């Protein structure tokens, strides 16, 4: 017979799936082992090898005694794991130095083996053995002994047991030259516990597990088919017909996909995905020491396989569109009819569902973070559980358990899906205790275990359990957007109306209560979550639309035979809308450019709009009170107003968002907008790089001074300069920064530079200059003083503008003046910045062959005050009769903090970012700017080692200072330790093509402290047990 066959098959297949799937984590795996030796080509030349883990698994080194005899009297590095002139190299690295009397080994601010030099060069000493491993950091000087102290007579071994004392390796640097001596050699064993590939056994077990689970579910299907019920071959009318709500939702989703905003964590996911295939494992790439997101990481591998085609924004986030359409179909054609005949008979409920799904999908679930996919999985789970309860079969329950497992394996906030299994638990238990009689217990229970457990074969493919435990150890040791509450405003009324009246005429109790309990359970899980509650709201997009479709029926006049309650509900909706129109931080970093309200709350007329909604709420509530006092019923006006409040509210918010985005596009057309760039991607577009402009050499367009008799200030002051002095700038003023006395991460080389220069400029200046300006070609004038103050003027010489041509005039849209002080100028974030006057006065050549002025131009001064920053003067605001131009500066403030400093102007020689950086140079793109710079190549990493970057792109000042500098600091596991220790940064002069007051971000050039070349690593392989760990990593002292 076939029933007994299917029983046996189900049992054996499910048990095998459970066993093998539990065993996948503990099974062996092949790891590639890299190691690094510094003398490579038999010559003493420096070498770079930036480890992303900021420490090796072990280090050994051997140094003869003769090398000390070869250096000069003032020797230096015999070797070091970072350059001696680097930033905090003596705090983060190993250094073997010779200070003219002592041969010192300095591990991180710790002096191990400090020994005289006249002994090491003697005839007794032979070698120096240095070893840093988990057992400690020790150094032995063979042939010698301790002469002084309590340790006298015993060997010259010295050091400390501390596994957190292992150095940070970004190379092997020295000061020696020539051939290599016999014995000098280091050996670093790099940590590569994450980059692996499976054995044949593990792979075969995973494949057999998936096959057996499929076999078991097929056999359980053949067992569920024992009842005479069948699926009819015809499709129903609802899946065949099409409506207008379908068109509205689909069109809105498409238009928002192209034109609309994007989430905040996009570059995070994109850079992880792009670097995963070269690495060999999904790394976070910004934090936590190259540790993976592998326990919740398979969607990222889907994105990584997608990146092999293109990295555009219109392709990599197609899953959002797919999942949106799937949610809409499953919600309109499987969720609403099963709630009852009332729902799916009305149109208002369908409009409510569609519009709420739109409004919740818009700010959050358009991007790359998987919140919308989680919502889709939860909806699929609910649908399959309801189909199981209705049809009485157990296969959709198993498929729903599988879907819940995967939805949890996307992101830890997928536990919402599991809530469905907690709601539809007792029905499935009833089914199991009902079918236990006909067929036994194990044929049913085994496939469910196999379904729940098959996720371990996908989640632990390229990883083991020890790696995951280590990654969690690091993540726990180190630390860790319009408001929408349609969810709550729809959960409260449906809840109270299901509690008030027991049974509703034409509505199902079970499905509604299950949906409501799902939502309450996940809100419970989320209030315990340390992250802010409002950020995780895209999970309630589809289920929230379902609850809205339910709520629009439980408040209509067909059930609520009282007007006062409906007016109260209207007051509630309007109060909610006011609370959502007030609390809005804005949009995030590229959608907030052309939006109407960028630095305020909405304000039309003469007072904010939230006040108008609170006022409408007040009228509604007082009207309800009057209805209560007149004790009337069934007034036609209320039946006209309270026909459908929720769809009207949702449509209002939808139209608001779409209008904001379309206004941002039309107001900001030729330069960057999300929609314009995405439309441009089909034609070879590259995003913000196409619009952003940069000066390769920031001294290229300095204008020629006309002839004149001038003073010691030079041509810049001019014929009566008062209160301006060439060295009139404070000690430490730098480019786009403030130079706090205590340091910060991710800072340029200008911070730690000296105060004064060794050689003065043309005029008697000593001030450093920001953007690579050579003080032998660029004068300065400033008014800061310390003995007594005075009112200061400056009116420079007429600087001859270049020429009168059209192509040149098109390529040269600016005249720029570098200045530091409190200067007035327009902007976007904060317009009309009050302060002192630095203006650009232009001329028109008279008929006598002589000059005479016409007017002035006011700048666009974006950037931190009182930093060295570029002041922008467009050439569109200048008449084409212009031939000459001068600076006019006034200081009418006797306070010691209101000071001015200026340089001469320049018509820069610009070009785009894509024309200079290209798509082959490595770049350190922060986690905010990856979706606008897709064509740029990030700094990959493979086998523990990274690539030395040549550039760094970053967001605006406050975001760089508050978000990225702190996230990927070296103390927390980021990449800026490597760059701060190995490289020296310098900020560049960048502009945006037609928004001269917008702060798109910053571009920084990296230069090398010392000349060096990449390393030739040595490879091998080892097979592990699955539970193997070579001790813990270094994360903390
Ligand atoms: C990767 C994501 C794939 C999602 C699949 C969703 C398909 C939805 C649209 C299909 C068109 C159907 C037209 C049939 C028209 C039709 O006859 O309706 C098919 C059936 C309802 O059938 P009838 O209406 O004939 O049912 C009898 C009733 O009329 C009487 O009550 O609806 C379903 O069961 C749909 C749900 C399938 C869901 C299966 C999902 C299982 C795979 C899980 C994927 C996991 C994703 C992981 C997380 C991201
Ligand atoms: C009831 C059964 C339902 C179907 C269950 C899924 C079927 C199995 C398909 C994936 C097995 C993994 C691939 C083999 C594993 C293998 O042999 O290669 C393991 C491979 C090791 O490669 P290396 O470490 O050399 O490099 C990989 C790197 O290049 C990328 O990280 O790592 C991967 O590529 C990670 C796999 C990502 C997996 C992406 C797929 C995620 C599942 C998508 C389907 C989920 C929805 C299911 C609907 C219910
Ligand atoms: Ca791997
Ligand atoms: Ca002053």
Image (cartoon, rainbow, N blue to C red):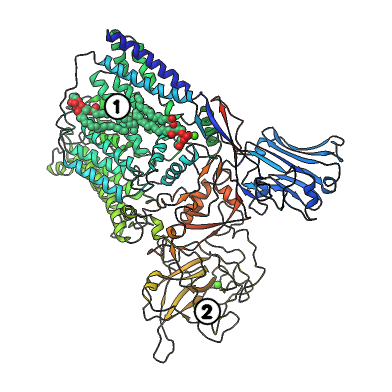
> What residue is shown at x 43% (from left), y 64% (from top)?
911
Estimate the x, y position of residue 136 in percent, counting from the top left: 70, 35
Judged left or right of residue 267, residue 760 is right
In the rendered view, would you say 894 is above or below 264?
Answer: below
Estimate the x, y position of residue 974 in percent, counting from the top left: 54, 44
Residue 793: image tag: 2
On the image, which quarter does residue 412 sit in?
A: top left
Identify the secondary structure beneath mark 2. Answer: strand
Q: Quadrant of the C terminus?
A: top right
Q: Earlier in the sequence, mark 1 or mark 2?
A: 1
In the rendered view, would you say 380 is above or below 80?
Answer: above
Q: Quadrant of ligand 1?
A: top left
Q: Quadrant of the N terminus?
A: top left
The residue that disc 1 covers is 514
Disc 1, disc 2: CB below 8 Å? no
Q: Nearer the viewer, residue 479 or 609?
A: 479
Judged left or right of residue 445, residue 765 is right
- Mark 1 Cα shell of 10 Å, populated few (<14), some (14-19), many (≥20): some
């Amino acid at each position: 017979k076939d029933v007994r066959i299917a029983r046996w098959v189900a049992t054996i297949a499910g048990l095998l799936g459970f066993v093998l799937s539990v065993s996948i984590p503990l099974l062996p795996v092949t790891q590639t082992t890299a190691t690094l030796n510094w003398p490579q080509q038999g010559r003493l030349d420096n070498v770079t090898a930036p480890l992303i883990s900021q420490a090796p698994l072990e280090l050994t080194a051997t140094v003869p005694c003769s090398v000390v005899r070869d250096l000069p009297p003032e020797g230096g590095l015999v070797f070091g794991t970072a350059p001696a002139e680097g930033r905090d190299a003596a705090l983060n690295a190993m250094l073997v130095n010779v200070t003219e009397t002592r041969v010192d080994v300095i591990v991180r601010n710790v002096v191990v083996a400090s020994v005289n030099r006249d002994r090491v060069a003697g005839p007794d000493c032979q070698r120096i053995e240095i070893t840093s491993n988990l057992d400690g950091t020790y150094a032995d000087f063979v042939g010698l002994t301790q002469i002084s102290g309590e340790d006298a007579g015993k060997l010259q071994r010295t050091g400390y047991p501390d596994p957190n004392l292992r150095p940070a390796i970004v190379g092997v640097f020295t000061d020696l030259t020539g051939p290599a001596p016999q014995g000098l050699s280091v050996s670093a064993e790099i940590d590569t516990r994450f980059t692996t590939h499976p054995t044949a056994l593990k792979l075969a077990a995973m494949l057999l597990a998936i096959v057996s689970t499929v076999i078991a579910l097929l056999a359980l299907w053949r067992l569920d088919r024992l009842d005479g019920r069948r699926m009819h071959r015809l499709i129903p009318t609802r899946w065949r017909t099409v409506t207008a709500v379908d068109g509205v939702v689909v069109g809105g989703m498409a238009i928002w996909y192209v034109i609309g905003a994007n989430s905040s964590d996009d570059g995070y996911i994109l850079q992880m995905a792009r670097t995963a295939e070269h690495a060999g494992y999904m790394a976070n790439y910004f934090r936590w020491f190259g540790s993976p997101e592998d326990p919740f990481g398979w969607y990222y591998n889907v994105l990584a396989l997608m990146t092999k085609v293109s990295d555009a924004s219109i392709w990599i986030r197609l899953p959002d569109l797919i999942c949106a359409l799937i949610c809409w179909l499953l919600l309109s054609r499987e969720v609403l009819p099963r709630l009852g005949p009332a729902v799916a008979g009305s149109r208002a409920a369908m409009w409510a569902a569609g519009l709420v799904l739109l409004g919740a999908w818009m700010p959050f679930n358009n991007g790359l973070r998987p919140e919308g996919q989680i919502a889709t999985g939860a909806l699929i789970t609910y649908v399959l559980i309801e189909r199981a309860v209705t049809s009485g079969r157990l296969t959709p329950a198993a498929l729903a358990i599988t879907t819940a497992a995967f939805t949890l394996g996307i992101q830890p906030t997928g536990l919402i899906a599991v809530a469905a299994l907690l709601a539809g638990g007792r029905p499935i238990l009833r089914i199991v205790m009902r079918r236990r009689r006909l067929v036994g217990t194990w044929p049913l229970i085994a496939p469910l275990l196999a379904a729940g457990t098959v996720i371990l074969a996908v989640v632990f493919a390229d990883q083991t359990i020890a790696t995951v435990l280590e990654a969690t150890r690091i993540r726990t040791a180190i630390g860790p957007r319009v408001a929408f509450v349609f969810t709550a405003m729809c959960l409260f009324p449906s809840l109270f109306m299901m509690l008030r009246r027991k049974h509703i005429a034409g509505v199902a109790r079970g499905p509604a209560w299950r949906l409501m309990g799902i939502i309450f359970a996940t809100m419970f899980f989320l209030m315990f979550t340390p992250t802010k509650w409002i950020h995780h709201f895209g999970l309630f997009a589809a289920v929230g639309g379902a609850m809205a479709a339910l709520a629009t029926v439980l408040v209509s006049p067909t059930v609520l035979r009282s007007a006062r309650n409906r007016m109260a509900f209207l007051s509630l909706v309007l109060f909610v809308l006011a609370f959502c129109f007030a609390s809005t931080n804005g949009w995030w970093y590229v959608s907030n450019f052309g939006a109407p309200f960028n630095n305020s709350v909405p304000k039309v007329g003469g007072v904010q709009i939230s006040a108008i909604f609170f006022a409408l709420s007040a009228i509604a509530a007082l009207w309800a009170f009057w209805l209560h006092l007149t004790r009337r019923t069934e007034s036609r006006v209320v039946d006209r107003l309270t026909a459908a409040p929720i769809p009207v509210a949702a449509g209002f918010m939808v139209v608001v968002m779409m209008a904001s985005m379309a206004i941002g596009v039309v107001r900001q057309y030729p330069t960057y907008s999300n929609g314009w760039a995405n439309i441009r991607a089909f034609a070879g577009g590259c995003g913000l790089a196409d619009d952003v402009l940069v000066e390769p050499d920031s001294n290229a367009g300095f204008l020629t001074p006309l002839p004149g008799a001038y003073g010691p200030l030079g041509p810049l002051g001019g014929e009566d300069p008062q209160g301006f002095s060439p060295d009139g700038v404070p000690d430490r003023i730098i480019a786009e920064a403030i130079r706090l006395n205590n340091p910060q991460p991710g800072t340029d080389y200008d911070w730690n530079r000296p105060i004064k220069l060794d050689e003065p400029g043309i005029n008697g200046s000593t001030v450093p200059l920001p953007y690579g300006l050579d003080p032998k070609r660029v004068p300065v004038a400033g008014t800061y003083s310390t003995e007594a103050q005075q009112e200061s003027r400056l009116s420079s010489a007429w600087y001859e503008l270049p020429a009168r041509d059209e192509t040149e005039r098109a390529a040269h849209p600016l005249v720029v003046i570098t200045a530091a002080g409190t200067i007035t100028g327009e902007s976007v974030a904060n317009g009309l910045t009050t302060g002192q006057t630095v203006d650009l006065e232009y001329a028109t050549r008279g008929p006598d062959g002589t000059l005479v002025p016409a007017g002035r131009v006011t700048p666009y001064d974006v950037g931190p005050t009182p930093s060295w920053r570029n002041l922008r003067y467009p050439r569109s605001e200048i008449p084409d009769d212009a031939v000459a131009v001068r600076v006019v500066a006034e200081d009418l403030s006797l306070s010691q903090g209101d000071w001015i400093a200026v340089t001469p102007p320049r018509v820069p020689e610009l070009q785009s970012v894509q024309e200079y950086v290209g798509s082959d140079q490595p770049v350190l793109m922060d986690w905010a700017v990856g979706l606008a710079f897709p064509c740029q190549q990030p700094m990959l990493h493979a086998n523990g080692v990274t690539e030395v970057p040549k550039f760094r792109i970053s967001p605006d000042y406050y975001a760089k200072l508050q978000s990225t500098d702190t996230w990927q600091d070296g103390i927390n596991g980021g990449l800026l330790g490597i760059t701060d220790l190995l490289l020296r940064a310098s900020v560049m002069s960048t502009y945006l093509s037609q928004d001269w007051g917008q702060d798109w971000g910053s571009l920084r050039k990296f230069d090398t402290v010392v000349e060096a070349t990449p390393a030739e690593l040595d490879f091998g392989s080892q097979t592990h047990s699955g539970l193997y760990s070579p001790g813990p990593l270094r994360i903390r002292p």
